Image (tube, rainbow over all chains, first blue to last red; front, side, top):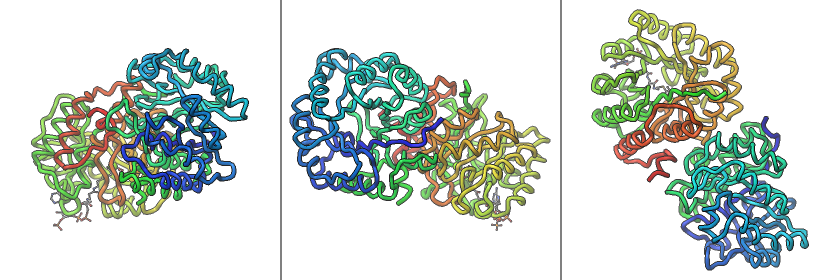
Amino acid sequence: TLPKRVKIVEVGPMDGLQNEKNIVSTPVKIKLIDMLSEAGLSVIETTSFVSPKWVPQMGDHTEVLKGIQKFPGINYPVLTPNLKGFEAAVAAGAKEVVIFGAASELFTKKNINCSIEESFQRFDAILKAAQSANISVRGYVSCALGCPYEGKISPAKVAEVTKKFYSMGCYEISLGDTIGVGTPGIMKDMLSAVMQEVPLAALAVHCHDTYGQALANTLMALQMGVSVVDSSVAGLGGCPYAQGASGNLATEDLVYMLEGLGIHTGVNLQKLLEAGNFICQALNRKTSSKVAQATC
Amino acid sequence: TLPKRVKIVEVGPMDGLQNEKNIVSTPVKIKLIDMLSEAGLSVIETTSFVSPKWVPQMGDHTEVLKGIQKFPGINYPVLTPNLKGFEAAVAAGAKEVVIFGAASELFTKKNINCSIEESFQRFDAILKAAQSANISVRGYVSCALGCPYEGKISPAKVAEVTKKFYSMGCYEISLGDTIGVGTPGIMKDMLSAVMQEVPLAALAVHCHDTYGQALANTLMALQMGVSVVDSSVAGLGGCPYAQGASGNLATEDLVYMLEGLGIHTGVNLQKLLEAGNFICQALNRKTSSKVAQATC
Ligand SMILES: CC(C)(COP(=O)([O-])OP(=O)([O-])OC[C@H]1O[C@@H](n2cnc3c(N)ncnc32)[C@H](O)[C@@H]1OP(=O)([O-])[O-])[C@@H](O)C(=O)NCCC(=O)NCCSC(=O)C[C@@](C)(O)CC(=O)[O-]
Ligand SMILES: [Mg+2]
């Protein structure tokens, strides 16, 4: 049955902002994050210590992590694509980092010119350094419900890559459907295989709403026992490998579904909505949250 | 568990066009319906034989029903609020009519201007005529998951009304979540109470996507065994007398989910999308179908 509590992983200021056409000032990023903490979120992916030469929207990573209020008990993980970035994250005060891979060979090769297996070597240093520093590492597997290049992805393959991340030291791995082509059965089959090798509590899903399947795919995940899901404030985000259609599952809409289900989230919807409106105005875009649209 | 086949009841030409300030021309309405016939839907709610006073957008019901092409196999149900309307429906060639009430007293008052018991009177008169003519009758129970006026609605209340419509002669009854405030748990409870009194085959769900819960609310129903669901093309819709009524689950996003689940619908997605694009340009609005947006 459904879990009693769900840990929402707010990715809006990171995954969301990274995939937005307009960029926002550093103070705006900081305000948004402070507003998400005040909304009650347990974890808020803050930024990415990535070469400003490859992704400018995240250029203020250092000053952002250092500028945000650190609410008691709230986690503020940051992406570290390589060892240099990991080092910059540590020096800036990061206590948790996120590394990423894919369950698809084609996707991996087109992105870093190496196989899935080879893509892990890049982490070994990060993984060992993080351990020597008492720093938590979150894993992420994209193409979990399908790949824009290979198409359908085998559950067994997703289970193998998640397993690898898990045994390498990732305390939690988030399964992603960034192109958003997944449907309930695909989610089910994938989770079923992954749960064989990895303990349920170490799992999370990150569904994009590109095809309007995000919430439905998420509920299936919840039905399978998963208790941590990723979402972006007001549906902020998008995928470079897909068309016009939106990106991330809207946090407010997920919260609305969980409150209705009587599932504890510890999030104040009213305040969450305020955060959503703030960043949307600063980004000059209409919210992608249906709850937001209907409420005001 | 999940049915191998689902009968999608397309309501775009009625419920979809119903709440729309700028009236649509008769030829456009006719054109939308033939295009939907083209896409392969097996049921298309054509129009409402109701007073032009309450809903003028539907005032051309007579000519619309007469002008559309009657494809082989496809059904073209039309709303009939009373014997007066049912009268004009049969004269216009209707092979199936739809009576509509609610589990809410206030909403009944404000929608069809009468009490719940009183609507049972009108309907009983319609079912009387229908039987002797073999003109099948479908029923609607609005506010199945809450009322914008009375708030919480009980599963027992919805089951009671549904039971009434069923015992009087309705072959099928659609449980419409008018304002889209429902969440999976609420949907499951309502369906369970209803299933005790009325057989599954005669049940259908009609979910609005005001809060982004339509697809997920619908998946819950499919898991409960319901095999017929209502939806509108480009996610158009909203009851003019529900207050705050947003669009209906987008038919394109529903077929995408079903096809994903390997569930037969008999609908041609590409052609459905064309129909969606057609009506949208006609209303001069952006489609609400996520799928349509990811296509181009
Ligand atoms: C029930 C009544 C009759 C109210 O009844 P009443 O207004 O209280 O008065 P009445 O019954 O004595 O007569 C009404 C007036 O309508 C006329 N009339 C009646 N039928 C016709 C006709 N065919 N052609 C020409 N005129 C007609 C009639 O001639 C008269 O006019 P007057 O002489 O004063 O001008 C109806 O008019 C009404 O209230 N309609 C509202 C429309 C409505 O209910 N729309 C919502 C559709 S349902 C929905 O959206 C929910 C659903 C299905 O989508 C699923 C879900 O979400 O749950
Ligand atoms: Mg409706």
